Length: 278
Ligand SMILES: [Zn+2]
Image (cartoon, rainbow, N blue to C red):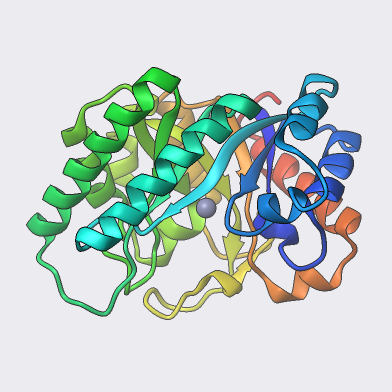
């Protein structure tokens, strides 16, 4: 299983240029690039070709672009924003050789029946799939374990992906999100491992579901998530391609970029290697 770094982990104490240097130095195989801040920032004094050249000349590679944000249940205008951004991301993936694009469900206070959220998510993901085919890029749906996220549990997200039924549409299994709204481990055990594109590892303080937010995450193994169950299930269903460490804890932004990157690696490797050869 390959090791990947998610820039959220050093959101406030690093930048893409530094993340690349340190992740490369510390044996990471992949990095997930943030499109809403890290990449634009990097592009202020670098070109996409510079970045493409970097990947061509170093071990580390770009696993995915992070977040086509709020793709489902949008009005005409919002849908336009989503499609326009995804089309733009396709060009970026092509230039940098990126394999995945993570998609995040709509977060809203509006109550929408599940069948409406499903129909919209399936229709939009199918449209994104159609767009991605000529680029060979795959879409990874990351359900978010938040009470205001329209798709917040594993089974709901899996049902959507299975209904889309496209080889280039899968899931991002994030341990925190799985735990955050109480997804059932049995649902994961019965899932097709091939539909899991990316595994985001993390952990969390033991607050009840509904109260949990991303700032509550802590390093893998230092929290209350039954990671043993998650890892055992992933192994059982055949997933084993990659694990990316994603944290949003303010506390860790107080560390240097390197301390965070090295700690993210050690905690992740020490937990995951008990189930997978890395
Ligand atoms: Zn995640």
